[PDB]
Amino acid sequence: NKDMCPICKTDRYLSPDVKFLVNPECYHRICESCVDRIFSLGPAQCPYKGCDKILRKNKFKTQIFDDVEVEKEVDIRKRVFNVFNKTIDDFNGDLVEYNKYLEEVEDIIYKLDHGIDVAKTEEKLRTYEELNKQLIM
Amino acid sequence: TINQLEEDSKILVLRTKKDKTPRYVWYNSGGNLKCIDEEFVKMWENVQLPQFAELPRKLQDLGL
Amino acid sequence: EYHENLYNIEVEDYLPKGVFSFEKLLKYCEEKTLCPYFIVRRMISLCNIIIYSYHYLLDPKIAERVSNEVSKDSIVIFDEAHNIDNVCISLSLDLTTDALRRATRGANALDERISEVRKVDSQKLQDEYEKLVQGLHSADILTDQEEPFVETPVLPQDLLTEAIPGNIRRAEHFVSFLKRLIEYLKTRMKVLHVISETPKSFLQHLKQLTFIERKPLRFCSERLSLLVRTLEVTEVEDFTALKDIATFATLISTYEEGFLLIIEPYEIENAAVPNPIMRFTCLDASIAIKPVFERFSSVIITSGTISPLDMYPRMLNFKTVLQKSYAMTLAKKSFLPMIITKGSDQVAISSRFEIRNDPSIVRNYGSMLVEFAKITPDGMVVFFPSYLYMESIVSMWQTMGILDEVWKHKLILVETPDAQETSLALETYRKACSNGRGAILLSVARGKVSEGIDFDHQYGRTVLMI
Amino acid sequence: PIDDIVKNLLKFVVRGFYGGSFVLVLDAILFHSVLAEDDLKQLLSINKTELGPLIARLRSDRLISIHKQREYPPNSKSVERVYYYVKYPHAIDAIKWKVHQVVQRLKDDLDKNSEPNGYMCPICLTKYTQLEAVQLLNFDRTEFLCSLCDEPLVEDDSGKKNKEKQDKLNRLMDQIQPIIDSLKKIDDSRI
Ligand SMILES: [Zn+2]
Ligand SMILES: [Zn+2]
């Protein structure tokens, strides 16, 4: 599974040119060969036994650090540090508050990031939707 | 008992199925594994070998 | 069990009056059951003369506990410090990706550890957050009587700051960015070619591929230090690597523009294999020198082989007073120097040509050696520019009929890379020289042999710089 | 060494997807690289049609490059033996390509797949595809006729090919823990 597509199991030995991609919907290890074939047609389920996440080839992407826990958190951070880029630490300056606001943003991020019980994260996602308004506000 | 523990568990060389299977020293892991489709094995046979060290390229040409 | 009983009696005042050399110290502390490692460690506070490796004066993570009693303005002696420069380069740091990978799991082992304990005993960790949210926590961010897990790779507990690591005050915040680190490193690991990165140049580049900030970056080590300090792990070999990351992190957080990170994608000796070396190194010795040098003007340096007396004031920029070269006074020969630029065939003999066999020289060198091996009484050593380079000479000589003839006269001892075998071999070489029948030793000038050992009359009568 | 694995791997394939007797000529001449041809024939003590077609595979796979082990005859005449000087590299080189080819008989086959796009009139027994159908379609006949047969069409390739390819996928998997893994176990040094 380390270097072969979880779908067709084409080893990097047998296809050295294999290029793995995953989707933000589910972050599935897979070769591009399936990727195109799967979504050259259009929005459908992920080709995983147990994945009925309907997803689309334009949303596809490339992992960097293979840490789907960090990367999602990175994505969560990326999602945050895109809108939660509206965080105020330098814009705040108060060393405790700049620490706190960072801690607050990170706690908001960690809530999304730690993801163990991410519904307060969904509440924070409401707050992130509120942040989508608060980064607007 | 030659083919009772078959699939190379008890391997032996059937010289013919009219000559009591006159055997040799035979023992293996899978040995026969006839479950592989003969046509696929024929297709496996159907792979023709290209030429010399260009084949070391040809496997790299073929994605090997 | 000594540091208890040592603490029982020792730590109110010293053992009576002796300057207890290891010969005296190792025994004397054994009798009263002391591991004097702590005896001196407490005695740090007492002695009026001290002696230790330059590291203990220069290695900031060990040269950290510098106290005014132990330092304030007293007299400084740097003996045989001709090679001080290379010592300052201490701040050396190369990255064994293979060890690094083990760190990743160690980081996960940490990741699991912090998560599992935060499941179980998170209050004191929150109390540690409260031990954090207060500020720098100088009470136990610095004072730990037997605890301190990670050393201070930074200068002797000076180059730090006070503003908290913002969010990272939460270890879960803190743990996360550490993974950002290694993965960034792991990301940086597999550069196709050699790449050299100045810190600042790399600095935003870090933020580029992953928006991390330098201000937390220094805080990692202490933040790590307390983190492991809170969780009493069963091993460090995983975490050595971990702290090294933090050590790296701190270092890369710390310095700039006198220091630089370079990653050769491998060791080119066996090139075209994956073994990249994310080497970040010191470049100027003087920078690490400056602090202790800054402290006291009673600073004194002398080697038996300082030459020339300019580079060190050049290289270290430091402000000397007098540098006098001492002509040894002799009413007699007392020793002999010689220079063999060419052999009997007047063929110039060299090593810069190559690491290889221009068969003229080595065949000429067999003679040179053997005739010397014949003439001298016991005790003779030779040096080689490099180990494997020497290896060539031996191997070819082994093939030639040279070696056996000298085997007739003397005994031969090679130098080994491992210290153990060497250490054994040397004493024997001493024994043969001390004993009647002659012997001979070979080693390398850059080698550990050339650095510590000494050669008297019987032990050394002739040397050779191949 | 891996050389043993090389011979080991040769045994596996010559016993995985080959019959049992295939490995007998392996071990026999694997005992000694330069071996007299009769010795294997003598110890096996079998016919020439029980040896000929087996010799075919040894050179059809080029695994046993039977070197003409010429000897110095005592009578001052021709002397030689078929000593199988194994060409370990070249033997596997085709094999890897051979393996690749059957995977092509699956990598191509992925397009022969699950959901029906084409059509066919059984009455003419002839397949058609989607674009023909819409070209053949009518406002009146919302479904397809067959200009050859004037006959409604039926989908195809839906069940069989999807079902087919998964079978070979396991057959493709059948080589995963086998040779290809051990092939990479050769790729470590590639000697
Ligand atoms: Zn695939
Ligand atoms: Zn028809």
Image (cartoon, coloured by chain):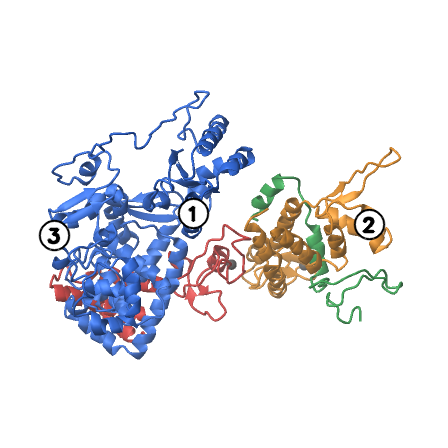
Chain colours: A red, B green, C blue, D orange
Q: Quadrant of the N terminus of chain C?
A: bottom left
Instruction: Please tell me whether residue D57 is drawn above or below residue D173 in the rendered image.
Output: above
Residue reaching furthest to the top: C346
Q: Say which residue label 1 marks.
A: C431
Image x and y of residue A11, in percent: 53, 56
Name the residue beneath numbered marker 2. Answer: D39
Classify residue C301 by image quadrant. Answer: top left
Q: Amino acid at mark 3?
A: Ser
> Which type of secondary structure does the marked residue at label 1 adopt?
helix
Could you confirm whether marks 3 and 2 are on the same chain? Answer: no
Q: Residue C302 in the image: x percent, y percent? A: 21, 41
Assign ligand 2 to one image quadrant.
bottom right
- Number of the label disc, if any, that sits on residue C74: 3
Q: In front of the other: label 1 or label 2? A: 1
Quarter of the image for residue C182 reads: bottom left
Is label 3 or label 1 in front?
1
Drawn side of residue D26 relative to residue C288, left or right: right
Q: Can the viewer see residue A132?
A: no
Name the amino acid type tagged 1.
Answer: Lys
Which of the two discs, 3 and 1, labels the residue nearer the N terminus?
Answer: 3
Front-most of residues B50 and A40: B50
Element at badge 3? loop
The image quadrant of residue C157 is: bottom left
**Is residue D28 visible in this depiction of the protein?**
yes
Subunit bearing disc 1: C
* CA separation in Å, label 3 and label 2: 90 Å
